[PDB]
Amino acid sequence: TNFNEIFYVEPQYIAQAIRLTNTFQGAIDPLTLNFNFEKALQIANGLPNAGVTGTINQSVIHQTIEVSVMISQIKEIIRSVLGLVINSANFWNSVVSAITNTFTNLEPQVDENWIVWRNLSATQTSYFYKILFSIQNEDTGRFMAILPIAFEITVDVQKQQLLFITIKDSARYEVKMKALTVVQALDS
Image 1 (cartoon, helix red, strand yellow):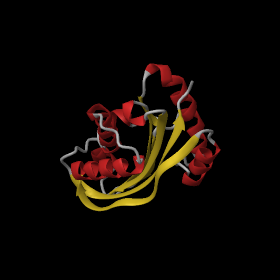
Image 2 (spheres, rainbow, N blue to C red):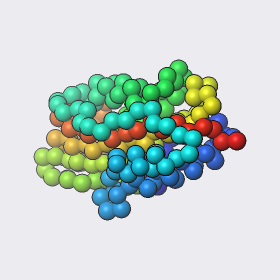
Image 3 (cartoon, rainbow, N blue to C red):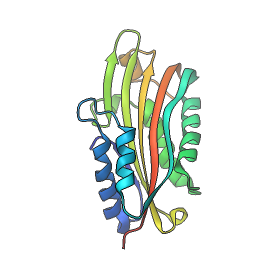
């Protein structure tokens, strides 16, 4: 499992979520453990009864920014990439918690499979961070939505300090985002 998996589905649909999450493991490079956008799109293309409702594959932050402001920006990007309107405050809570844990609370996550440390110099830290949402509720109707998200994050903070960075801190971030939303007809 190379993704931080976040299931927001009814229990009766957990099977489908597991299947689709398993399927997207195939987009992980075996060596770098980066997320491969092209491969994720190939995988999406092969799925039955499915369509892609949004994608992104580009840099989304490249500046000095407060971590909270960055998180808010990425929430709005996720809103766009979803290509579905989910009204649930709790769903959006799940999303924002996951985005927050991409940049903060890194100390407890240091050895988790979903984070990949790369450059760890005196002047810079870079890492990959991967999240996978499965989503099914009233606003997905007859469908489940699957949203794999990978970030490539470079920040001008040395690792030891980054492990304790908070939403109120600022630093110079370079963040590349690769994501797609695929919807598949529910599971009978």
